[PDB]
């Protein structure tokens, strides 16, 4: 399980793609020893902890060890001005932004396919007993149209209410099954094409709203089937919610007959459903 330590000047920034709660992403370039290769790389400087500890080095290593089809591998770390996580640059950027910008050229197939992928993405984390804590359409990236990866897993081991399960809002109890809740929302985010969860509603009302039995609404292109999946992810009781295994199997079952479960109009015709 090999982590790369990268020099402060083996790393050169171009621009800023986005700053969140934790740090700031930079599009960057990386020149390993010599003058032969130049990657396209993505740089994550965290601004406050976390300092160059063995404790730090331990958690980095774990993260370096994280390895999927559908998970973003940490490539390297620099320490020199402060802590910097180095990631292969995803040219298409984040899925959230992606489903908005191509709203009209994204078929059913991809949509369910992304589902599966993130599902399997999480399976692994679950199998490795890592709890992401912060799954949303933003922190899923797009390597290629048919290929998405998850990022930002375990970032709180180093260092989002509308994607939080209820038990994490009250009792900050962070579990795989609390991530499940997140997934629910993430996929919802896709079906709507990038819709904003609980739109035009304040933060501090979310919890009581949920407790009432009000959840996120049915997306336009959704058959009740796939919606019932979602619903199950926002079950008050944690254990009652699905395991990533299941959610995979299900969306994977659905990607065999794609338009059987999601209906998308335009093309001058009106697709009609049954049963």
Image (cartoon, rainbow, N blue to C red):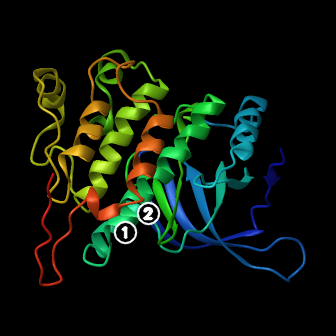
Q: In the rendering, at what x and y percent does residue 192 appear?
A: 22, 58
Q: How far apart are marks 2 and 1 (CA)?
A: 6 Å
Q: In this view, does 160 lie above or below 72?
A: above
**In this image, 102 relative to 130: left or right?**
left
Tell which of 100 and 228 is nearer to you. 228
What residue did someone put label 2 on? 94
User: Which of the 4 image quarters holds residue 87?
Assistant: bottom right
**In this image, 134 relative to 272: left or right?**
right
- In what element is the residue under mark 1? helix
User: Residue drawn at (15%, 51%), measured in percent from left and top?
Assistant: 275
User: Residue drawn at (26%, 63%), measured in percent from left and top?
Assistant: 193
Q: Residue 88 carries which label?
A: none
Tell which of 36 and 252 is nearer to you. 252
Q: In the rendering, at what x and y percent does residue 103 appear?
A: 26, 72
User: Residue drawn at (41%, 43%), measured in percent from left and top?
Assistant: 250
Q: Are marks 2 and 1 in contact (CB under 8 Å)?
A: yes
Q: Residue 98 carries which label?
A: 1
Q: Which image quarter is the N terminus in?
A: top right
User: Which of the 4 image quarters holds residue 259?
Assistant: bottom left
- In what element is the residue under mark 2? loop
Q: In the rendering, at what x and y percent does residue 130 appear?
A: 59, 31
Q: In the rendering, at what x and y percent does residue 112 appear?
A: 38, 57
Question: Which residue is farthest right?
Answer: 34
How many neighbours does mark 1 have within 10 angstroms: few (below 14), some (14-19), or many (20 or more)? many
User: Residue drawn at (60%, 68%), measured in percent from left and top?
Assistant: 89
Q: In this view, does 125 lie above or below 253?
A: above
């Amino acid at each position: 399980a090999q982590l790369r330590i990268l020099k402060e000047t083996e790393l050169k920034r171009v621009k800023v793609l986005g700053s969140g709660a934790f740090g700031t992403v930079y599009k960057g370039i990386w020149v390993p020893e010599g003058e032969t290769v130049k990657i396209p790389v993505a740089i994550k400087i965290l601004n406050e902890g976390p300092k160059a500890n063995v404790e730090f080095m331990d958690e980095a290593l774990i993260m370096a060890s994280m390895d999927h089809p559908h998970l973003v591998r940490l490539l390297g770390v620099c320490l020199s001005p402060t802590i910097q996580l180095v990631t292969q640059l995803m040219p298409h950027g984040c899925l959230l932004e992606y489903v908005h910008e191509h709203k009209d050229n994204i078929g059913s197939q991809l949509l369910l396919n992304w589902c599966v992928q993130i599902a399997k993405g999480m399976m692994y984390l679950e199998e490795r007993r890592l709890v992401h804590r912060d799954l949303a359409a933003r922190n899923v990236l797009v390597k290629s149209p048919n290929h998405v990866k998850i990022t930002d897993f375990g970032l709180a081991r180093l260092l989002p209410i509308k994607w939080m399960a209820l038990e994490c809002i009250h009792y900050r109890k962070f579990t795989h099954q609390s991530d499940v809740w997140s997934y629910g929302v993430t996929i919802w985010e896709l079906m709507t094409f990038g819709g904003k969860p609980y739109d035009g509603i304040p933060t501090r009302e979310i919890p009581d709203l949920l407790e009432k039995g009000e959840r996120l609404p049915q997306p336009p292109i959704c058959t009740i089937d796939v919606y019932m999946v979602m619903v199950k992810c926002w079950m008050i009781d944690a254990d009652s919610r699905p395991k990533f295994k299941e959610l995979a199997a299900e969306f994977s079952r659905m990607a065999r007959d794609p338009q059987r479960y999601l209906v998308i109009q335009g093309d001058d015709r009106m697709k009609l459903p049954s049963p």
